[PDB]
Image (cartoon, rainbow over all chains, first blue to last red; front, side):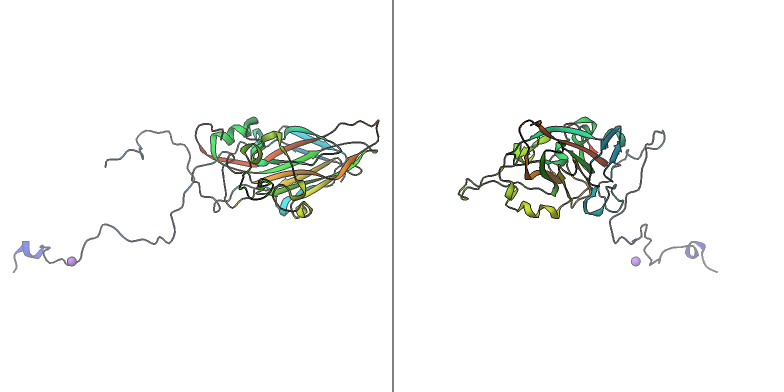
Length: 49
Length: 244
Ligand code: NA
């Protein structure tokens, strides 16, 4: 009855897909206890600006 | 109650003529809460290697002595492992157990006022006339382990009456009664941690209110020794050793 590319079409979506959400933050984040970590595979310090 | 023993670290103090123990402001030294702290790095709590009795220089009580004082974080900054930690770390925190000892005989007499004065800021005589805005030298504000002698004990070299110095944790050494004073001081400051080099939390004052006296023939050398032990020492903010 109606062409498929029109049915499955997404032209018209008025809602903005947001990848992030606003969370409550009434105070500065806390710090948690940390111990030594001697391991391979996990590298928190290495980034890619 | 007249006898006592103070053991902490690998050091023990004995006394058979004590006068109880004073706990400054009714509080025992304690470590810093997780909600009172700010520095996020994990502190060092060396325990036994720094929380022990260190015996500083001895002073001689003369019939004409005026009194002496010692600034506290300071007196220990160049001694033992406590000093090393105080130099290597930016932040320091701790309480103290101060034991001033001085014995004589049943024929000598005199009374020393041993008190703890927090934030003991030293002033100058202002050139005598009071028109010169002079300031106390580093050698006087932070005398080290050798302590410093008071020039005008009546005003504690700071324009305040010594007669009211008893509103501070204190104890007396009355030769006819006891031969030592023990005062336990908690960490007192408006910050959870602070520098052991730039700031002196309090000062120890030993002042003769009733002059020493005795008849010729009785030993004339009457020493006053200061022994003190840090308590619940914590250090943070590690770096290279800094002297000042
Ligand atoms: Na939209």
